[PDB]
View 1: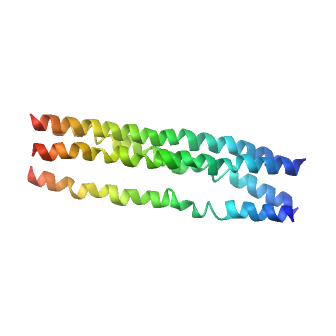
View 2: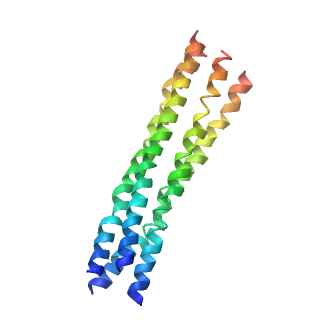
View 3: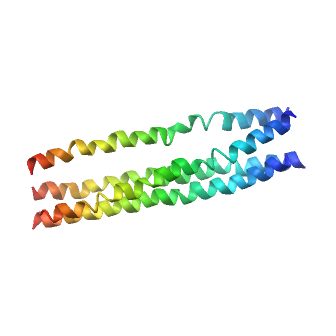
Length: 49
Length: 49
Length: 49
Length: 49
């Protein structure tokens, strides 16, 4: 019962949290999609120049 | 002895990455404000214009 | 159990070292962002002149 | 058999996934220099002021 409880524990962490892991780095990659867009306003300055 | 050693191994050194993940969490997050502050000098750029 | 305890021990160190050291790598991105911030001051300065 | 399989499963994956944290940490940290050089191109605009 203790070994099955440990098995449930290591599942509850390692079977789940690493798969959920995208909440850092995955949702972190979305920084790209919303930093990049400073480039949308890079050219408008140039157009003015 | 070996199973309790493994149990200690995970309870200390798997639990490590939940404990230590706060480092790449925090110092990964804090890139936010310390990029953001380009906006402090963006306004002086506008004021130039 | 013994060999996995040993391998999880080493995996502890070999994940703690990255997740701390590359948090200081996140601080690298902070420092580099601050260099962008610093040159984003020189822009307004010569702008103002 | 099953406990050694579980043991090997955890050993093989902890010597993998959180050590492989070097992927998110590395290619995350390396955002540093390759954002940074917006500064080396910031100075050319100051030269254009």
